[PDB]
Image (cartoon, rainbow, N blue to C red; front, side):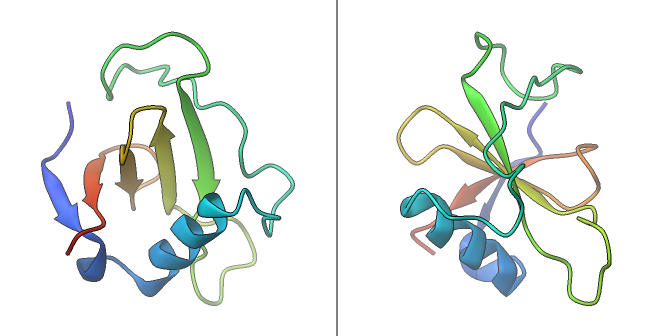
Amino acid sequence: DVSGTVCLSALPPEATDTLNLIASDGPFPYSQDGVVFQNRESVLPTQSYGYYHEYTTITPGARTRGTRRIITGEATQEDYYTGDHYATFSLIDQTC
């Protein structure tokens, strides 16, 4: 289940960076950014394979990809933010 919606302005600034890169189709900091997100645990709504894709939201100071990500849905303006490594997701509202 999705844990509600959240304004983009309320998320870490890096989330905005991630969305800006997605808007230009990259290039991304990680060649892996853009791979399909399987939604294996069915936390997000059920969709066919390839409907979701994941991108890294950089965590300052981290040597690894960290726990923050933005998962895109193919629908218009459909983007999910997770800050706990895919445990929970919140729909991102870019209008606020």
